[PDB]
Amino acid sequence: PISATMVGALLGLGTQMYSNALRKLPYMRHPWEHVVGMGLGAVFANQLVKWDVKLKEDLDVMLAKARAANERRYF
Amino acid sequence: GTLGRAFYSVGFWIRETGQALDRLGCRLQGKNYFREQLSRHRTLMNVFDKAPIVDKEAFVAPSASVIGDVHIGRGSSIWYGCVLRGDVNTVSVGSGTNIQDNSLVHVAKSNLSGKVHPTIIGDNVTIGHSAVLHGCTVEDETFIGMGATLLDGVVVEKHGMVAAGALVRQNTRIPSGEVWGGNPARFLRKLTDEEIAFISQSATNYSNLAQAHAAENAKPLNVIEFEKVLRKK
Amino acid sequence: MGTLGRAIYTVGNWIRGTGQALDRVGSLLQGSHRIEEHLSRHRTLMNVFDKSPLVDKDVFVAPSASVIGDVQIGKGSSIWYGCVLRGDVNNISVGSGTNIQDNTLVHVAKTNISGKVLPTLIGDNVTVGHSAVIHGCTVEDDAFVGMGATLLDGVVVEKHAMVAAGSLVKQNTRIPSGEVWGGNPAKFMRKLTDEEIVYISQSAKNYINLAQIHASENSKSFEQIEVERALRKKYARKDEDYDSMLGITRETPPELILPDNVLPG
Amino acid sequence: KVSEDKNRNYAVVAGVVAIVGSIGWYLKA
Ligand SMILES: [Zn+2]
Image (tube, rainbow over all chains, first blue to last red; front, side, top):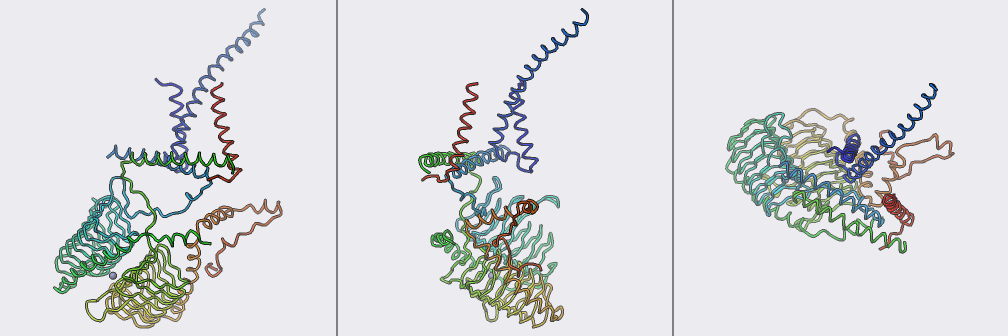
């Protein structure tokens, strides 16, 4: 369906064409750069999803510690 | 159509990539000649599928510009500095017709001012130096004077003559055997039989002069001038 | 240099081969519709009917100009961009210090309809404006032809005579000295003042100066073109403040400085 | 026959080493 790799590749393609358009160049001015941008976008999206998972995992442990400290007050 | 235009566009992406690759290969070998400013002028230029079709006997000067759908017949000639643009509509030139130096035969660039009329040039027609023909029709054996301007919708009938420097306004029909001149062009006098003989003899002569010019331009490019330009200090 | 240089050279050869193959594949995908650009076949100076143009040493002929056949151009003259001097059926003579401005056509006639057919004669210190048409006529020395004017066969423009811009001068018309003619057809407009004679002379003298800079630029080789491109880039802007901090003064190189005779001052 | 700019050759080798090292870095991580 809709995966991180696909969204990232599409966003990398969009960035290169957006960058070409901001410079008033043709959309496909340097197409190898479009290939590079798709690759980079896919890499970045997969890494971002993995990083989000790791961050949630770490936040769970830290909230566990916070709740333990707060529950210490009622002893 | 759309599929051909998509393929033409994707081909440009592959070509631009290949040309960049070639430039990379030269940069690795320390060659910079790809940076030389060389003229990109093409005598016959295409706009996607619209390309000029030129008879093998028709002389075209190397500095002339023939753009888009432009038909040139046998024995015709396009002289030095001439510009023929056939993008928004077609330009057709009949057999044995001379377009003299620096002439412009073009169609309307836009349809804002109405449907874009094509330009039709008949057979054995003389178009004088630096004349401007824009979306008109010129019938067989007519004379267009040097520096004349024919706007769109103008009909020049057979054996009709437009004097030099005449501005023929839009939709102005020049009847046969009539000399029209001035700004705007109006009837001036009736054409004489000697003038008709001179018209035909002139077009026959220009076909023979064009043959001469087409031969000297065909000469192999001098390697001596090439070496002189290369070795300048 | 050495083994590493040779290895990189071979790799670059492979890269160029691949690039050209990719270019061909893209061309095939385009449907062979695109007409390829080729080496330029325009000849600035060309013979015809075994007649060779005779051009003086210090004459600026623009590379885009077409000088064909039996054409003679004198010292200090200038043939600008897009000019066509086709002397194939007859003789074209151009005097000294005469400018033929951009996109002008000069032609001759083998035989006119009536009268004696004559070559195209242009005298000394004559100005011919942009996109003029000079056909089988005679322009005497120190005359003025406005831009977009058309002179037909037999026209004679006398010394210190002016043809106004856009004029259509009918066949065998004579423009007398000290007179300005104009219109379609051309006709007498008024007399020429002394300030206007001075203007004509100063026009020819200004164009001899302009011809020098244009001739210098158009004859530069690839190596010099690249050197001056780099220089122009290096001196386009300035940071005189940091120069003063460094104790240096950056000077414009002489190859980028125009002669004083072409500057507005 | 030979490329003579030695600094350019060194830079070419450096770019090649960067690319190959990036590939190996990914493959062994
Ligand atoms: Zn002519």
